[PDB]
Length: 135
Ligand SMILES: Cc1cn([C@H]2C[C@H](OP(=O)(O)O)[C@@H](COP(=O)(O)O)O2)c(=O)[nH]c1=O
Ligand SMILES: [Ca+2]
Image (cartoon, rainbow, N blue to C red; front, side):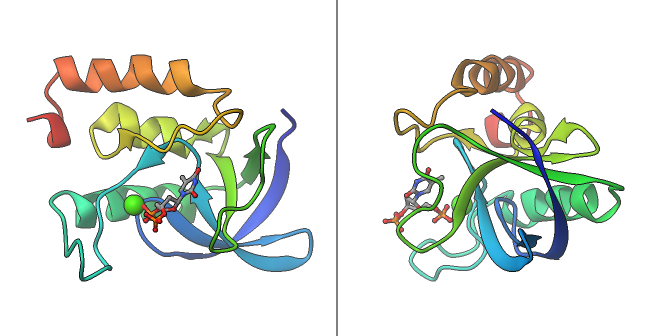
């Protein structure tokens, strides 16, 4: 996998944001995780949703460098959102949320699963430490 620079346009919620990639604005959705809903009426404002959103926002807003890393399978989902592992100053946002108990490992679609085990070990840690979602 190769990391590529991007520029933050707007953080939307815990796992979706708009970035300027390859000269064009695109909304991105973090690979392999799921932060709680704060938008969709069918799900309503789920618990920790606002929190996951605050965590992500702070993280990407205060970063000097943002990089996107596509996996080896498809690069966009059915809604046209880019699918990637996002890094804020070298720290993977996907992992950070999981480790904090603000996201669950989900939507594991082969072959876009290169970092699955890494994210799972962090989630098991958040779980045993009964953090947020796991409390
Ligand atoms: C992370 C991810 C999301 N999705 C889809 C599944 C879900 O679609 P449905 O709308 O059909 O449930 C939705 C989950 O993202 P959200 O958490 O943003 O809803 O996006 C994929 O298609 N593949 C992925 O790798
Ligand atoms: Ca979500």
